[PDB]
Amino acid sequence: SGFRKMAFPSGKVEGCMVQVTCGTTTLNGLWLDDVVYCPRHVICTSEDMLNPNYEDLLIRKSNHNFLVQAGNVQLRVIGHSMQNCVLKLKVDTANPKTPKYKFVRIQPGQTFSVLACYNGSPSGVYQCAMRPNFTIKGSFLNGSCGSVGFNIDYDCVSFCYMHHMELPTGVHAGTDLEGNFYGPFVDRQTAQAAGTDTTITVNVLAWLYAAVINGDRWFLNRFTTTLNDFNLVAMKYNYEPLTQDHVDILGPLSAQTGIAVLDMCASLKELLQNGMNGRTILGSALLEDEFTPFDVVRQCSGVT
Amino acid sequence: SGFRKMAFPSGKVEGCMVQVTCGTTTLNGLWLDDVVYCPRHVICTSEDMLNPNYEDLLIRKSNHNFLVQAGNVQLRVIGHSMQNCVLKLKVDTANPKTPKYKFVRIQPGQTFSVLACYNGSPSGVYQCAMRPNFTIKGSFLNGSCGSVGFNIDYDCVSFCYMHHMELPTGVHAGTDLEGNFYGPFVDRQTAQAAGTDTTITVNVLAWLYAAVINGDRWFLNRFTTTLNDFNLVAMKYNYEPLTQDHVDILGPLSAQTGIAVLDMCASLKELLQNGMNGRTILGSALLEDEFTPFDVVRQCSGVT
Ligand SMILES: Cc1ccncc1NC(=O)Cc1cccc(Cl)c1
Ligand SMILES: Cc1ccncc1NC(=O)Cc1cccc(Cl)c1
Image (cartoon, rainbow over all chains, first blue to last red; front, side):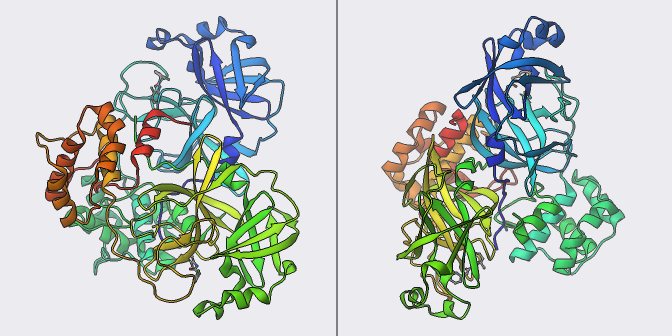
């Protein structure tokens, strides 16, 4: 019993964190096999960030200008290349701590753990969601760039995110491990708009199922609804429209609790229209959307 | 910018997790140097838990009855002893992954990271507080017993908690690494009362300081208060009385923000008396008490 915002154990990722220095800028890199991945803005100075020509900037750099340090040992850089917004530094040594891994581009609404790092050293781990507007509400300071987001399936680490930038609104933006930004963001010191962000409806419903399982049932009512009626309410409250695909992934939780998905939707509809009236659900006074249906199943069954 | 419920990187602790089996019961153990620590209830059957005589139960067991498995390799048990509510299994091999460590008994209101484990395998990491009533609101299932709570200071892991029991109210109880329970709990299948739990006032004030630093300032008002006036309000709302010691630890945050501690108390007083009026602070619709003043300083400065 109990429900927590749980992150994956960060050990396999800690063994991959390195510090990358280029000139005066230092940030985090990910050392997998004989390649170090880091944000390409490591090659910029503060003046460059206003409007960087990354190709021209990288041309003034050689293998010896990239200082890669793993813990306390220096790695020899024998190759460098830019792929989208990431730099790939070929080193002469394969990381002995390289776990089984994959690079994956996650979908908005999906969750992942973040290992926040400074100077190649891990400082903390937290669980977050990729917002529908492709931003993350992380906790990152200067020096955190290159910190990564991941998921773990038994022994395989699926890297999904690399931190690049804090928008003027305090929210965060980054790339997949191929250097493609999630969202319309560019790695430039210019005001950039994150779109209107919506609440991840399917995740809120999954979290209401987690609440029923853990004993918080006060919100369950004698009502039901339809996908069309519920979506009229979701639209009014800036919730993502619920589709049959979302209903299908809620199936295991609906089977476990015996509460049909559309019945849970009617509870959510009443919570949206009436608020919580000063009550809490799973220790929260608001509707939580950072737990996918898979996260609820994993946590509620103890998957290691 | 941004403020998250961040846990310590769990890597140094993952390398210590083992599975301990005794008869038909399996739970988690902590392998440090040549000793495996686990809850003593590993020696009980379901029938024993109603009223166990642990000394009599342990006498029927020999070194060979304790099956300790680290990952996939078996450890040879050469000694066994009971210290309070923990079993200490001497193994013939020192854990090569033993980090620098200490055993510490934490105070109520202090925070720590938990590495939830099943069959000696880590499944998740979350940050929590030891409640003033010595319980923790964790996320633990059957098989999680022996999962540990810790803090990390540079390279030293301070182990502070071992999970033993879920109370009939869904809250959790456990021991320090010397087997002493936090609270009045006994490792027995009997209804046990956790006292009245209060909100950790100093942690809420530290979190309001984290809010001001990150931009959420709407709650700041034109008022001030005294320790005695504030404590009258704290008493009414079941908040821990604030002492000069608490004011002293809030000093660094007060210096950083330029908001005197008693001015922050007046904001908290108005929030307690008026609620949030539908607003949020750091993405929360309630007053958060799981961040100590040290956690706010560490997170807001990027301590690795
Ligand atoms: C200071 C900080 C805080 C949190 N995360 C990240 C940062 N750093 C930056 O955003 C630096 C920067 C500036 C313009 C473009 C890019 Cl790609 C990166
Ligand atoms: C089932 C479960 C869920 C979460 N944490 C722990 C558990 N397990 C137990 O509480 C088992 C037990 C029973 C009576 C006394 C003691 Cl010390 C331990």
